[PDB]
Length: 395
DNA sequence: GTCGTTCGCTACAGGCGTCGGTCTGC
DNA sequence: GCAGACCGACGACTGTAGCGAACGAC
Ligand SMILES: [Mg+2]
Ligand SMILES: [Zn+2]
Ligand SMILES: [Zn+2]
Image (cartoon, rainbow, N blue to C red; front, side, top):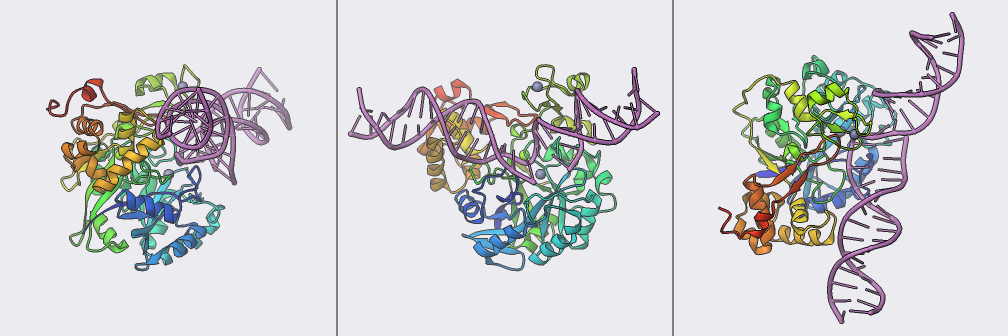
């Protein structure tokens, strides 16, 4: 079967995350969005595991079901050097064993969803490998809490340890990361990093796997690419929409080139804020090869359908109008990705003509994109002539 | 024209580095 | 004067009350 799975979210026990991020609400919104598989997130927190065991039914020792949505155990943890890592756990026993292993190195393993571990990246990855726990750098190019803001290579961070994937990130796609030859031997995950069950948050990115069943072991085979299983698609935000795509100030969000930031010594001259290097500049800084791996699954660039509806209707992202139109589209067609990429523009027009024209302009690269940077999300705008013209005249 | 309903924007919440400024024993 | 210890604030890890003000079915 072919399923869509988002393997990096955060519960309400994490920080700066909506209190609505509980198993029932997450499952409801994932089902509404057409999301087959969702990572649990924060699995090292015992209270979140208790809530899981409460609101779920067992599929196997590492797969659970809430309101028809499947869940495998995942967690993001922070390094001794302030570097985030994503981990996928085979069974609940691996979760509990890892949790007990790091209690002597952590002070918030029981009170937080994103724990801090007084362990280096190599130590964490080695402990995971010893327990067959899938480990990988999460949002690997963020200028604040990623691997590549701390290290110049995966080898410098993990040493003799092994990773099982690399989480791309909102502000990057597969080609950018594949500009580093090492990455060619590593599977990519495109996950949402959702702090909210909102439509444009939960499942903003995901991975499309081919599996026999929806279980942890099938997903592990799909990530490894063995036994006929495979990651056949990586759906993700257009890298320009991420918060850290370009190099900009952390306070006023004004964008600067890499040369300009170097000459300015990383302080914004118009607000005194700290300029943070974008992932595009960072990857070009670490650029290695012009080749790509052949086995690399295609990356489908997305823009959240709620954002399209908000820019068309000229209203806010949380408005009731965009919510109603988004629900109409989802009831009618079943998934955001289908409306964005797969559905014919004529069928989109039956629900809303302006949204159909905007989606056409998105598919045909005729949409204005103000790239994000320094912590500000990218903005999406549509030229006026697109909305003024008729559908049959676009092409 | 009324008055519930809805919108959009600002302020603010909360448990380990970085980054300026300050104090301290020479 | 000054190196170096000491210190406090600041923001990522972003979401949402909540408050004027505009809207929209009667
Ligand atoms: Mg992306
Ligand atoms: Zn993280
Ligand atoms: Zn600035």
